[PDB]
Image (cartoon, rainbow, N blue to C red):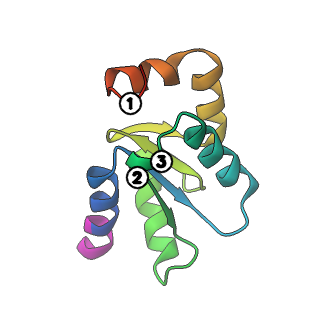
């Protein structure tokens, strides 16, 4: 499906911070909360792909893009961050803040 791929692409390209998530997902909630803690709300889009008829297609495409089909899947300025664990590593090690500084998202 070109359609599914184009829809996912639009989400990643039109939002600096793009998070693909599912319903009642602790790690999705944690990742989104960490990102909102940097006051990134205005440039964040969260897509619940479980509430979607094409969940499997979306997950397969996210795996083609990132190596994993699991949610959360996190992109920042179209770059692959990965899952919540990747986000936690970047956050603890200063990489996330550097990412956001280069985007003028954090002082």
Residue that numbered label 3 is attached to: 41
Is residue 47 shown above or below 16? Answer: below
Residues at marks 1 and 2 touching, judged by CB atoms closer than 8 Å: no
> Which mark's residue is nearer the viewer, 2 or 3?
3
Residues at marks 1 and 3 touching, judged by CB atoms closer than 8 Å: no
N-terminal label among 1 and 3: 3
User: Under tag 2, what secondary structure?
Assistant: helix
Is residue 39 shown above or below 97? Answer: below
The residues colored magenta run 1-6
Disc sitting over residue 62 in the figure: none
Residue 81 lies left or right of residue 83; in this view the side is left
Residue 107 at x, y percent in the picture:
41, 19
Badge 1 crowding class, 10 Å Cα cut-off, few under 14, some 14 to 19, many 20 or more, is: some
Mark 2–mark 3 distance (CA, rounded to whole Å):
27 Å
Residue drawn 42% across and 43% down? 75
Mark 1–mark 3 distance (CA, rounded to whole Å):
10 Å
Mark 1–mark 2 distance (CA, rounded to whole Å):
28 Å
User: Under tag 1, what secondary structure?
Assistant: loop
* Front position in the image: 59 or 22: 22
Q: Please tell me whether the stretch drawn in magenta is mainly helix, strand or loop.
A: helix
Disc sitting over residue 64 in the figure: 2
Residue 45 at x, y percent in the picture:
43, 56
Q: In the picture, which quadrant includes the N terminus? A: bottom left
Residue 31 at x, y percent in the picture:
63, 44
Residue drawn 58% across and 74% down? 50
Residue that numbered label 1 is attached to: 105
Residue drawn 30% across and 65% down? 5
Residue 47 lies left or right of residue 85; in this view the side is left
């Amino acid at each position: 499906s070109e359609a599914v791929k184009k829809w996912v692409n639009k989400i990643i390209e039109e939002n600096i911070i793009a998070v693909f998530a599912k319903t009642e997902c602790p790690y999705c909630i944690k990742a989104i909360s960490i990102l909102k803690g940097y006051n990134l709300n205005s440039h964040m889009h969260v897509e619940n792909i479980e509430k979607n008829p094409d969940m499997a297609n979306i997950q397969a495409y996210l795996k083609e893009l990132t190596g994993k089909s699991s949610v959360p899947r996190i992109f920042i300025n179209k770059d692959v961050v990965g899952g919540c664990d990747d986000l936690v590593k970047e956050n603890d090690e200063g990489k996330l803040k550097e990412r956001l500084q280069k985007l003028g998202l954090v002082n």
